[PDB]
Image (spheres, coloured by chain):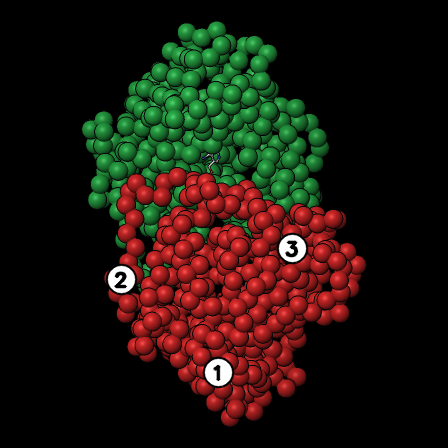
Chain colours: A green, B red
Amino acid sequence: IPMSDFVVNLDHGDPTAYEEYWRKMGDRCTVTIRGCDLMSYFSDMTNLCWFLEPELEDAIKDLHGVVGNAATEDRYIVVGTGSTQLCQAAVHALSSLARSQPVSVVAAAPFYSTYVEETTYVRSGMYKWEGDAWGFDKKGPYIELVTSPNNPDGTIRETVVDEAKVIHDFAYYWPHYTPITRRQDHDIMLFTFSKITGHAGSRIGWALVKDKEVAKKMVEYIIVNSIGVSKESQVRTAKILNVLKETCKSESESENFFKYGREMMKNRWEKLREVVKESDAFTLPKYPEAFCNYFGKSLESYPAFAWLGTKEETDLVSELRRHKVMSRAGERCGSDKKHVRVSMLSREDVFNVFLERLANMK
Amino acid sequence: NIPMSDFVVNLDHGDPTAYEEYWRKMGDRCTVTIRGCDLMSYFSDMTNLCWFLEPELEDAIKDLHGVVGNAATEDRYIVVGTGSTQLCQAAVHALSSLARSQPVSVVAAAPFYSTYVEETTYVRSGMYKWEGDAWGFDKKGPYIELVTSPNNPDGTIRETVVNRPDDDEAKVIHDFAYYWPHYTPITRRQDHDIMLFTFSKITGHAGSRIGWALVKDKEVAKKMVEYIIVNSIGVSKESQVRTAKILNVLKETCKSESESENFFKYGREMMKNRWEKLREVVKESDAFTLPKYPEAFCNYFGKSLESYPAFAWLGTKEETDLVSELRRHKVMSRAGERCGSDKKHVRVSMLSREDVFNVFLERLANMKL
Ligand SMILES: Cc1ncc(COP(=O)(O)O)c(CN)c1O
Ligand SMILES: Cc1ncc(COP(=O)(O)O)c(CN)c1O
């Protein structure tokens, strides 16, 4: 079997890039759970989010503290089974408190394809996905989704359209990906564990929510949806997240996660960048340089996804399938046939194989 | 310093803390160890229809049913979900999806599991409508029937009740969350189209958030899976690995003839002890009723024996709101009106800690007196 017939799967952003890193960290990352632990449905009935584990709460807030990307004071924390359940909890919670329904849900194009799935699959009478925000005019209550750094195109975003409301999805707003220009302080701020460290099968995200009443409804949603979130997932995320925090007080460019992650993304993007340059069809986006409060230097953005473009009237997702490279169709993301989103967080060898095949075609 | 007369006894939720002592005394053999680089990927197994299902856990489920003998696992799919809670919704969603017209009606024989009302109501879906009590139901069209046996709240063994053909557009979901030897005799190896189980209610590990569905129709199975994908991109990996570990111990325990090692013996002995106690109180009390449960032959234990369900369905001949009366004694339970019954019953959980159970018995004897 040649590495011409091997399918390189860069459609999903399964973040496996980070595995060797975590392997190396050895015995301190380990989580030990005994037969009788984590048995109860409840964590703490004193918290608005009663199914959130204290060690995890502390870890989340400590971590936004050391990095300085989001405000965690005077606001409620809600955990979900990935940020996926969290964005839907928020949409359901904000829809519940709107004067009237359906509430229009929009996001600037190109947007995170999954959003169209999340807002469409249960055929709920509470909210209606209304496509691109730029092209959104419609009256009545709406919710805007703002992914920054964006998915697919990695751009830094702000809103674009008075009681209607907004959700900020800052899943990729970490120092290894983009500079920390500012400590965010918005009404609803969504984060995901999978994207910081690569632990995607842990299924953990969190929401920082200012409005007390929105936090309450997100919670109710989750309780009816899954009665909360895996305790052991939460205890594990805590340990890894704590280790990541101890890692920040290190000079080692192989211990310090954010200086490990960032170098890797730089190395990966500089490589992809050669390939694209010495090629006649392709186009990557241009990323402004910006000062980083965390790193204390002025540096470039290296997004988890490459928005791969074509200048010629090709149907770019299909061409890549033909060379055994799965990508995410641009049409899926409110773009056009000339664009693909390719994951930049795969393993070394897969990424290389991907570059190799990107060179070896017309 | 707070008198025990101020202690609230919460028998409303069914938090199964009864089983902690047992798992503690099992010690290290139960421990689960997970290293920094484990379980990182979204995917478990791209071969399986449910690609987010950990093989260690598929094996455990299949093994456990193999041994207990309560459900058929052959020639069908296994869909893991975050609790049985996510799985029933996935099922109603899947069967509705595959229906000739929507909304599909969703009914359940009363008394029924209250949380069903919220689960098929909270997102105001176009695909299905909650139609309440299945008894005498004949709204013409596609319908799903929920059959929970042993039932919640009343412990009853159940079969479908709306049994018009409505041909092939009559669908059924079986919730066998309490069909285990420590609660009820295993009279038949269940072989229905959709069978749900929850890890919570076997061993008490409720915060693990683990249930599974045994699904015959692939088209339904694939739809449950797609619902879970969008809903939550699968189920916590470490939850799955930890559920498999303890399930496996549970299984090892089954050959043990020690009354205190063997889960189902211990489990059963605990339930019995508690129902005997509660039954004494209701007997000597003046105003209380309790359901009668037939004796039946258990294929697992090989003996004819009683059910001791996880919930007590407490009633009153008297004309009072029983949920209110218990509320005045700092005993919380689940309103019978919430389960499609009347003010004269409430559901109380038999699965609390030993001390809490006892304070409730103490209080129960002191009632109306
Ligand atoms: C914009 C965006 N939102 C959310 C998700 C992550 O959701 P989860 O943590 O539920 O996997 C991703 C990919 N990890 C994403 O790119
Ligand atoms: C009938 C019934 N079904 C399902 C649930 C189990 O749900 P979960 O998977 O959320 O523990 C329960 C609570 N044990 C129940 O009583």
Q: Is residue B147 above or below residue A60?
A: below
Indicate which disc residue B305 carries: 1
Q: Residue flagged by tag 2: what amino acid is it? A: Arg
**Mark 2 surroundings: few (<14), some (14-19) or many (≥20) residues within 10 A:** few
Q: Mark 3 — on which chain does it sit?
A: B
Q: Mark 2 — on which chain does it sit?
A: B
Q: Is residue B64 above or below residue B346?
A: above
Q: In this image, A2 relative to B142: left or right?
A: left
The numbered mark, 1 or 3, whose residue comes first in the sequence reads: 3
In the image as oriented, which residue stretches furthest toward the front?
Answer: A1
Q: Is residue B223 above or below residue A361?
A: below
Residue at mark 3 shares a chain with residue at mark 2: yes
Q: Residue flagged by tag 3: what amino acid is it? A: Thr
Q: Quadrant of the N terminus of chain B?
A: bottom left
Residue at mark 1 shares a chain with residue at mark 3: yes
Q: Mark 1 — on which chain does it sit?
A: B
Which mark's residue is nearer the viewer, 3 or 2? 2
- Determine whether the residue tagged by mark 2 lies in a helix, strand or loop: helix
| One can see residue B135 in this view | yes
In the image as oriented, which residue stretches furthest toward the right?
Answer: B140
Q: Is mark 3 within 8 Å of ligand 2?
A: no
Residue at numbered disc 3: B121
Q: CA distance from mark 1 to mark 2?
A: 31 Å
